[PDB]
Length: 144
Ligand SMILES: O=C(c1cc(-c2cc3c(cc2C(=O)N2Cc4ccccc4C[C@H]2CN2CCOCC2)OCO3)n2c1CCCC2)N(c1ccccc1)c1ccc(O)cc1
Image (cartoon, rainbow, N blue to C red):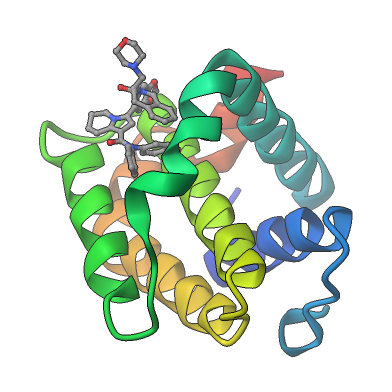
């Protein structure tokens, strides 16, 4: 199947933020299994690297004017050597962490921007690989 990558991003971020006590109203609402499997994969990745995640918080020092550069720098590093599902999970978890950090640092408007930046990058740079590699349904089989 083929999905709406914007919807995948928005659902992923909205859930992560709602869990943590922020209702992201600007971003409020086979597909179902994709959303759930991606969330669980990201949570597994967060657990797997729990202490590196904890530590990362201090590394980024986000501000509105630097946030895009900080985001893009990491995304470029993640995919410099090509695409695979692991790096896609890392990309979703990184975006989600950036949204949580934006809320925590009293910069909640950045959530909307991060969601856009993630969607643009999926659209432009990852979708061909996803489609070629069996789509999100292949991800579900591999991670489910
Ligand atoms: O710089 C990064 C980062 C995270 C990964 C990464 C991606 C993966 C993965 C693995 C790692 C990884 O390399 N780590 C995971 C991790 C997780 C959380 C925080 C830091 C790190 C760094 C190291 C952990 N080390 C690796 C060597 O052995 C000891 C543990 O398996 C599947 O996909 N990679 C990078 C940079 C480029 C190589 C891969 N972040 C980053 C971003 C901002 C600031 C600092 C680091 C980043 C990117 C995406 C994320 O979801 C989270 C982190």
